[PDB]
Image: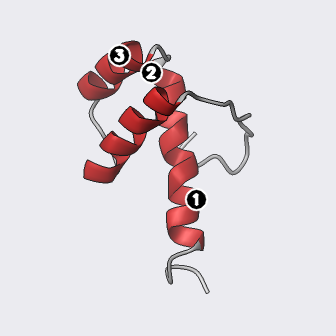
Amino acid sequence: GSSGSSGRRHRTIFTDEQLEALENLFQETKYPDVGTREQLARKVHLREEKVEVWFKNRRAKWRRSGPSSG
């Protein structure tokens, strides 16, 4: 649960609009609020759960590319 190390999650494609919002939120705040997520989801025509996932994916790079690792 905490970290997606044990379990695996598949990825899905999104539209420019959907991505925009997501990136617009993840950019301002790495970890949004249940209220913001639920709303954003319906706003981008997505499921809260999915929304949260996208964020996790982004972080992956933010660390890989960043000096955080290596």
Residue 2 visible in this rendered orientation of the protein: yes
Chain-order first, disc 3 or disc 2: 3
* SS state under label 1: helix
Q: In this view, does 30 lie above or below 21?
A: below
What residue lies at 58% left-to-right and 39% top-to-bottom? 1
Which quadrant of the rendered structure holds the C terminus? Answer: bottom right
Picture colour scheme? secondary structure
Q: Is residue 16 left or right of residue 43?
A: right
The numbered dot on residue 18 is none
In the rendered structure, are the residues bearing label 3 and label 2 in contact, judged by CB atoms less than 8 Å apart?
A: no
Q: Quadrant of residue 39?
A: top left
The residue tagged 2 is 48
Which amino acid type corresponds to the residue marked 1 in the rendered image?
Ala
Chain-order first, disc 2 or disc 1: 2
Disc 3 from disc 2: Cα separation: 10 Å
Question: x, y (%) of residue 47?
Answer: 49, 17
